[PDB]
């Protein structure tokens, strides 16, 4: 029931970083994301875009269990996103759909402008690994901490690769 | 547990010269006083991540380069750091086989390919083509012997026939393997398996034939030919048989394209003996004395080490391995290799047995190896959606504007493909 947190800062207005994050994947800064399928999009009473997206992934930590497990491959990610342009806030929760029962990994991202005003964006991140059969080990967890921290860091670079286009 | 410090533990396949490798280890311990243990666990290529991910496993893992990318992806392998003058002693295309993401993840040991191996007393003139082997078998079976026997359990052996008329693993271009494009269910892959399957279906081979059965028979003069690799020579040498190693045959006029392997030594990310394993591999293994010690046990193939390869490339057996190796491709090191090998393993065995027809088997293998986004069929409708939405999302939404979605029509059409897409899966 562990964590990995972060708070990155992007050097562009909130608008463009959100325009980016909404057309993020697939893209060359993260080739482990095979593609993103938007299953449902709704605007709510408050004017916030709700999307349900299902991602197709590769070498993320539910594949690290295929090591200890024995044999498998493709891992699917449920994602719910809400963007409120009035409140200037983008939220995003994700879970693994397949290769669960073993481990479940819950990420959560929030893009928002810097509280001091510099036309720059700050993203606040966390990942919640829970597992039944809680073996792990600090080594395996460090592996998981490391691979989480890379999709994280590749996700940002994926933004910059988009907003510089 | 955590690996043992002050000790080197080594995994290498049991069909390789491990008693020789053990003798390099002894030379190391005799010299450095650091004990070395050489084991050969079964299903080695699967068990290493199973324990090197928990911090366990061997200090040094010995396998073909094709598995080592999957390992580096999951950070199971330390990055190896030889100096410039040490990598000048190894052929640089072998290093190429162990560069993942521009990082070196293993020491290359030796280039391996499959060659044809035949009994000369039984058969003085080996078939130049697969399509003539049924006859060879019908004429030899009349003398109680048989034509061919090579190990159907591992797809490594039956692949150069599948690759012959145009099967491949993934498509290579632009410095990248396209993991989304897999040439295992094309015409020139169905045709090769259908031949093998027909060999079986016609009692010319046998679907149960594994490494041991095929090795036993060829060596005991029971079958005229085998397919196998350099490691296998030292048992025919110690057999009556007067063998020849030669170029593989051809299928539909095309040569057999073996998946070339580069036996590689990987250091474990979890090893507290990393500097001890560098010393072992660089200064005791990749020496002519080191490599000869191994190569005299079971032969290594064309070693990666230039100085020793000079004496080696004189062997007519090495020449024939290299003939076949140059008629095939180097295996890629990408993490999808295992899904590839598993799919082919399943397809061939299931076709060979009858549980699946050929087209069934390689259809299944198309999808199990492809790694496709669920809605790959509909990318063209998402592309024209996405353009509409990103335009709406930017201009009539992010800057406040009201009017409901102008992209509802394209969405629902794409929503239809992606909903049949999910249903045809899970
Ligand atoms: O059959 C699938 C395996 O193919 C190769 O394994 C070869 C290996 O390279 C060779 O040295 C060894 O002795 O024989 C096996 C076939 O049994 C790949 O390197 C493996 O990744 C595959 O599992």
Image (cartoon, coloured by chain):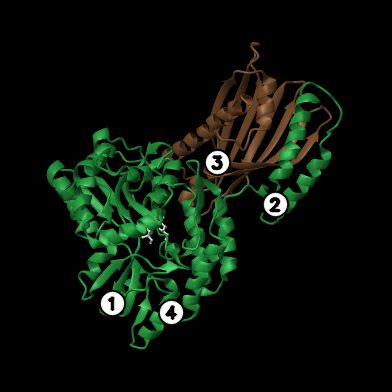
Chain colours: A brown, B green
The answer to whether the residue bearing label 4 lies less than 8 angstroms from the nearest atom of ligand 1 is no
| Figure quadrant, ligand 1 | bottom left
Residue position for label 3: A32
Do the residues under discs 1 and 4 have CB atoms within 8 angstroms?
A: no
Q: What residue is at 36 percent from the left and 81 percent from the top?
A: B146
Q: Does any portion of residue B15 appear in the rendered image?
A: no
Residue position for label 2: B422
Do the residues under discs 3 and 1 have CB atoms within 8 angstroms?
A: no
Quadrant into which the C terminus of chain B falls:
bottom right
Mark 4 or mark 3, which is nearer to you? 4
Mark 2 and mark 1, same subunit? yes
> Callout 1: 10 Å neighbours few (<14), some, many (20+)?
few
Mark 3 and mark 1, same subunit? no
Earlier-in-chain disc, 2 versus 4: 4
Q: Distance between the residues labelled 4 and 3?
A: 46 Å
Quick check: B340 left or right of A17? left
The answer to whether the residue bearing label 3 lies less than 8 angstroms from the nearest atom of ligand 1 is no
Mark 4 secondary-structure assignment: helix
Q: Where is residue B160 in the image (x, y as percent from the top left)?
A: 43, 62
Q: Distance between the residues labelled 2 and 3?
A: 20 Å
Residue B124 got which mark? Answer: 1
Residue position for label 4: B134
Q: How far apart are marks 3 and 1 (CA)?
A: 52 Å
């Amino acid at each position: 029931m562990k964590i990995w947190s972060s708070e990155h800062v992007f050097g562009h207005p909130w608008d463009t970083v959100i325009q980016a994050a909404m057309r993020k994947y697939p893209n060359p800064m993260n080739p482990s994301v095979l593609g993103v399928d938007v299953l449902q999009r709704r605007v709510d009473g408050r004017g916030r875009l709700h999307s349900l997206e299902l991602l197709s992934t590769e070498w993320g930590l539910p594949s690290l269990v295929r090591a200890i497990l024995g044999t498998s491959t493709l891992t699917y990610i449920r994602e719910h996103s809400v963007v409120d342009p009035v409140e200037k806030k983008m939220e995003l929760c994700s879970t693994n759909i397949t290769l669960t029962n073993l481990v479940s990994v819950n990420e959560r991202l929030v893009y928002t402008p810097h509280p001091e005003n510099p036309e720059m964006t700050v993203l606040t991140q966390e990942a919640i690994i829970t597992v039944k059969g809680i073996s792990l080990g600090s080594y395996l967890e460090s592996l998981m901490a490391n691979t989480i921290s890379s999709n994280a860091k590749k996700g940002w670079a994926a933004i910059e690769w988009i907003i510089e286009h | 547990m955590k690996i043992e410090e002050g000790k080197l533990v080594i995994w290498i396949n049991g069909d390789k010269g491990y008693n020789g490798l053990a003798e390099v280890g002894k030379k190391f311990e005799k010299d450095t006083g650091i004990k070395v243990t050489v084991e050969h666990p079964d299903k080695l290529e699967e068990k290493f991540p199973q324990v090197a991910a928990t911090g366990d496993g061997p200090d040094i893992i010995f396998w073909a380069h094709d598995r080592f990318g999957g390992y580096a992806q999951s950070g199971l392998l330390a990055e190896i750091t030889p100096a410039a003058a040490f990598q000048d002693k190894l052929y640089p295309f072998t290093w190429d086989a162990v560069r993942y993401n521009g990082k070196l993840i293993a020491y290359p040991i030796a280039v391996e390919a499959l060659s044809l191996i035949y009994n000369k007393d039984l058969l003085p003139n080996p078939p130049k083509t697969w399509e003539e082997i049924p006859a060879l078998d019908k004429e030899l079976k009349a003398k109680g012997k048989s034509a061919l026997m090579f190990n159907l359990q591992e797809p490594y052996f039956t692949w150069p026939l599948i690759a012959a008329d145009g099967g491949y693993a993934f498509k290579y271009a632009a410095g990248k393997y396209d993991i989304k494009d897999v040439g295992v269910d094309n015409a020139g892959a169905k045709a090769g398996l259908t031949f093998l399957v027909d060999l079986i279906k016609n009692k010319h081979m046998n679907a149960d034939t594994d490494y041991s059965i095929a090795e036993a028979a060829f060596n005991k003069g029971e079958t005229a030919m085998t397919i196998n690799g350099p490691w296998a020579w030292s048992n025919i040498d110690t057999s009556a048989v007067n063998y020849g190693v030669t170029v593989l045959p051809t299928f539909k006029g095309q040569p057999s394209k073996p998946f070339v392997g580069v036996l590689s030594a990987g250091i474990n990310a979890a090893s507290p003996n990393k500097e001890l394993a560098k010393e072992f591999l660089e200064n005791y293994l990749l020496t002519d004395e080191g490599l000869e010690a191994v190569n005299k046990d079971k032969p290594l193939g064309a070693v990666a080490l230039k100085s020793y390869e000079e004496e080696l490339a004189k062997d007519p057996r090495i020449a024939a391995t290299m003939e076949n190796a140059q008629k095939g491709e180097i295996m890629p090191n990408i993490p999808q290799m295992s899904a590839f090998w598993y799919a082919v393993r399943t397809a061939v065995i299931n076709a060979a047995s009858g549980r699946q027809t050929v087209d069934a088997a390689l259809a299944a293998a198309q999808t199990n190896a492809a790694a496709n986004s669920v809605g790959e069929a509909c990318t063209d409708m998402k592309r024209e959606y996405d353009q509409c939405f990103n335009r709406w999302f930017a201009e009539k939404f992010l800057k406040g504007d009201s009017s409901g979605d102008p992209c509802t029509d394209l969405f629902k059409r794409y929503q239809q493909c992606v909903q049949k897409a999910i249903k045809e899966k899970e």
